[PDB]
Length: 16
Image (cartoon, rainbow, N blue to C red):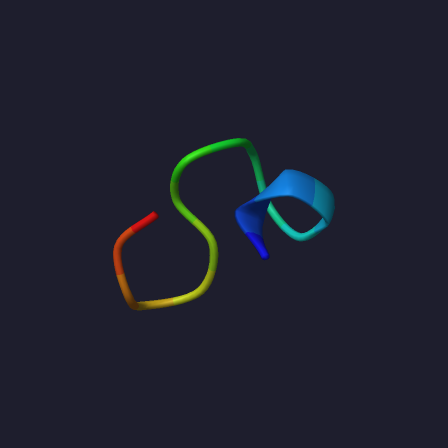
């Protein structure tokens, strides 16, 4: 979800 959430790998609090 990091793709369209935060950056690329890292998303919320999980990993990526």
